[PDB]
Image: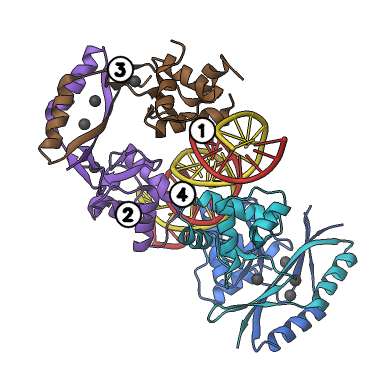
Chain colours: A purple, B brown, C cyan, D blue, E yellow, F red
Amino acid sequence: VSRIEQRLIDKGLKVTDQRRVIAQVLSDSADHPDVEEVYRRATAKDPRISIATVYRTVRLFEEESILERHDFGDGRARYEEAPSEHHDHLIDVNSARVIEFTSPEIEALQREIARKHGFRLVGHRLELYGVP
Amino acid sequence: HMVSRIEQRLIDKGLKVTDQRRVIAQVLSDSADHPDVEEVYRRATAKDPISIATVYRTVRLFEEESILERHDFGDGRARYEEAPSEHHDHLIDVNARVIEFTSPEIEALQREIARKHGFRLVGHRLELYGVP
Amino acid sequence: VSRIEQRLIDKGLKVTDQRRVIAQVLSDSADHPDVEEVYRRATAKDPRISIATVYRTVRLFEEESILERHDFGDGRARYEEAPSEHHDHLIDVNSARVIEFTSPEIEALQREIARKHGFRLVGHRLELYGVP
Amino acid sequence: HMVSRIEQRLIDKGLKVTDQRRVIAQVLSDSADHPDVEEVYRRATAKDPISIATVYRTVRLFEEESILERHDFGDGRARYEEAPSEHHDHLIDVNARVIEFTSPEIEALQREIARKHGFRLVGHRLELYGVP
DNA sequence: CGCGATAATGATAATCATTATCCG
DNA sequence: CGCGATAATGATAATCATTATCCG
Ligand SMILES: [Mn+2]
Ligand SMILES: [Mn+2]
Ligand SMILES: [Mn+2]
Ligand SMILES: [Mn+2]
Ligand SMILES: [Mn+2]
Ligand SMILES: [Mn+2]
Ligand SMILES: [Mn+2]
Ligand SMILES: [Mn+2]
């Protein structure tokens, strides 16, 4: 077996060839690509693949914590393979590189801001725009 | 109060002020909250003629021209507000009021993160989502 | 104006950039391509294009006699720019070339076969499979 | 009549004849019409246990093995029949009975068209659609 | 004429026939 | 095990917010 299939086998999901390929595509990606970009990269590896399927997988994979959905501004949701720890993003406004970053002190403050306004933080989003 | 903060900005920016641009300028200057475009249409009919096509065109120009801030609060439609002289961020009740806040310290850290990466931050999006 | 836009202008349809491009794609095509193949060829000419739009156009263009829909066997419908006269197809089973062909005597026989079984022929389909 | 034309073909072709393959073989040998897969399922339940998954798998094998002819009559589902010793073609009531026919002369011409093109025809699809 | 009326666009979900997975 | 139960697939239509076209 492999990392993709094992997750699916353990998560009670049917391992299909396309789920496998989509999984692999996200696996060796540097950038955060939109759903089409995944569809293209998948169909390059294995043609037996629908856009409808690439949409159905991302939703599920997100629901199952196998991949994270971001939304950096443009209509398109960008997708990345869920990482070992949470990370936020710093977008270079010039040559649009993305920098993953982690800050423990912030998440705390953020949950403190929740418990101040009588809230429980079910999720957050932090993106920082920058220039050299 | 006879010419709104935003109508003043159009004037300064040399852009032509139509009765509808004026009306939507009213509505946006009025609002402490963050209406979607539909609410900006309703709020603008409670004053004058204004078409939907138009309300759309306008809140776009305004946004393009830095007069407005567009928010996506994970609920379909875009939501809008006048560009705040006093920067705030957003806690969203996932169930649906949007409490605005400022953490002088989250700001503090954000600046450091960008510094510690060799990037001066020129904007950021920080949103919190939760329940009580 | 041009051939595409004139048809649309005369057919009471809004000329959009994508309708224009899709039209052009079909215009300089040798083969009969599926909807994806059109989507790819379109996006090569002008990126501002949805698959959903490429689907919506083909239906309309067919409904408006601007392009013909065939179905040569595989799931995919193939599409060609509606020609000056009806033609049927001869598929080379070896190196899958398609040969357009016209036969007046057959259509007659076909309408005779209609009027024999008390029918009115609203449409037909003839494809011939061949080898050298 | 105890082993059907089609069960005989499996036997000859060395393929394994299961009770369900046998039953669907019955049903297909029985039918003068052209049932969709659902009707082939109903007709096969009116004899034995047979699952839908299975009816699908079978009429596919049969079709793959040249025992069956698949038709698409422009109405969603595929429709099926035993491979006729006597070739016919199809007039479809667009409103929904399918009268079978033979034009010894359309056959005549088809052969010529392919000849006049330098191709021996090894199969053809000719369907007529109409109302009274 | 920048606007209104309105239909087209685009991202993505839905539908439904057919297909593959999994399991016993 | 080729099968049943069932969910996944693929082509394509539907939805709905936003956008462009056209016209006066
Ligand atoms: Mn964070
Ligand atoms: Mn990331
Ligand atoms: Mn902030
Ligand atoms: Mn605000
Ligand atoms: Mn013909
Ligand atoms: Mn043709
Ligand atoms: Mn024939
Ligand atoms: Mn028949």
Question: In the image, what residue occupies the spot 17% across and 30% down?
Answer: B110
Q: Which mark is residue C76?
A: none
Q: Is residue F4 above or below residue A64?
A: below
Which residue is tagged 2?
A20
Q: Chain of mark 4?
A: A
In this rendering, the label closer to the viewer, 1 or 4:
1
- Whether discs 3 and 4 lie on one chain: the answer is no
In this rendering, the label closer to the viewer, 1 or 3:
1
Which residue is tagged 4?
A52
Q: Quadrant of residue C28?
A: bottom right
Q: Residues within 10 Å of mark 2 (few under 14, many from 20)?
A: some
Q: CA distance from mark 1 to mark 2?
A: 44 Å
Q: Chain of mark 3?
A: B
Which amino acid type is shown beneath numbered disc 1?
Arg
Q: Tag 3 or tag 1, which sits nearer the N-term?
A: 1
Location of the C terminus of chain B by quadrant is top left
Instruction: Report the front residue among D25 and D110.
Output: D110
Which SS class for mark 1?
Answer: helix
Q: Is residue C85 above or below residue B100?
A: below
Q: Chain of mark 2?
A: A
Q: CA distance from mark 3 to mark 4?
A: 38 Å
Which residue is tagged 3?
B100
**Beta carbon of the mark 3 residue lies under 8 A of ligand 4:** yes
In this rendering, the label closer to the viewer, 3 or 4:
3
Q: Are marks 3 and 4 in contact (CB under 8 Å)?
A: no
Q: Is residue A122 left or right of residue A109?
A: right
- Image x and y of residue D14, in percent: 51, 75
- Image x and y of residue A21, in percent: 33, 56
Which residue is tagged 1?
B57
Q: Quadrant of residue D100?
A: bottom right
Q: Residues within 10 Å of mark 4 (few under 14, many from 20)?
A: few
